[PDB]
Length: 246
Length: 245
Image 1 (tube, rainbow over the protein chains, first blue to last red):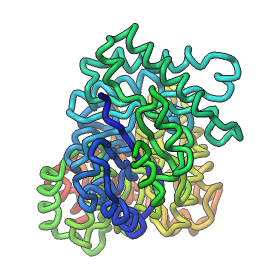
Image 2: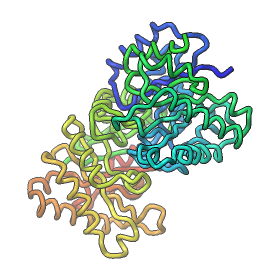
Image 3: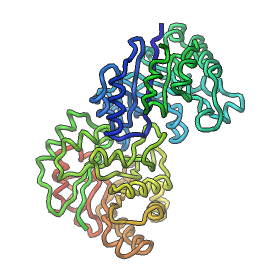
Image 4: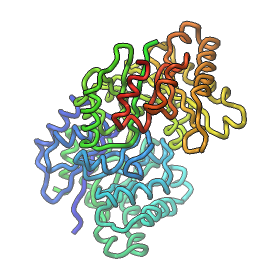
């Protein structure tokens, strides 16, 4: 019985005043008890957000590096994330992979280390438009998921996020049925390559375009276990997406 | 040119350990002729500014080139200002050589940070292969050039020379080898920008500095301070603050 999971990726948006407002909205919101809600602030505001947010909402970092301390100007470690009261980290996000060039190997290593330090991990995967139009969706997301899997001792604190990069900013839209086709193929990969236990208990959430209007239909897909929300996570509309199963 | 001592904590510390360091720094007597800046890890910019006495300025360790946007894991100069920090380090050797940040990207970041009202510590330097091939000047001049082309105003910039060729290589820089590069960089400012920019721009040294070495390095005519690494996490940093005393 996989617990429904809604992530809010704020990305590089907001200041203390505006995020303070957003947080007041989320605190005033009724969160269903059967739903796990997580918010990822810009790294400068992880501490700030954890202090202001009600305990019913967990806090994620948006990225981290692969050792606990070191000569890595501009990076943060999982220890720092935990030290700030955050319990999750988002890793392998399409923007890290495709804007900032983070390799599969680097990401697998980040997952191992964040997991070894006690954080949950939202591990992101997905294919670009050129990869999808070349017919290599499965090949790409399976390879990304394999590299993550090779750097794991334990699956219980991982959530997989499928991002259709091919449908973010390109003009193309993704159907609920296309999302479901990728999600069930990823679950089938977990069953045949890790275990049926992992396949049946691991949340696979959809990180493509989600709104107050699209969320109910997407969430009723049997292999779509929730959402990693982009722009809408900055709006009160997020509260509708939290309630997508209601 | 006011003497400038920067402390780059890198990816080190927690609230407890950094709170302790900050107590130590808050007890230090900062000379009137010296500008002190500390760069915490990004998760602790806010924490550090709240705990530090105002006689010490706070810097971000990196930032991005737009004020808000779809850039998971980044921070903007707006957020840095919002947390009470007045500087950012850009083009650090680690951003360049571990994380692949290009000259063009760094230039764009410099322009955006200066425009949003931050000071910028702009880092340049050559690797060992480049030094031993004889292209020290080519590499550092190119890096300073691409930056200069993305800037109009020089008053809020500090140039940091990093002898990357001395990090974990088995080679080290002498004070004289540091002076030599600082002099050539001031030379490039004269010839490529102006004499005025060349006479007023702090050029600080970003290689190994300790309490034992700091006074000899600071006495070099073209070395105007430091961007300190490992020693910045220790009381020894307070002695490096006193380098020109």
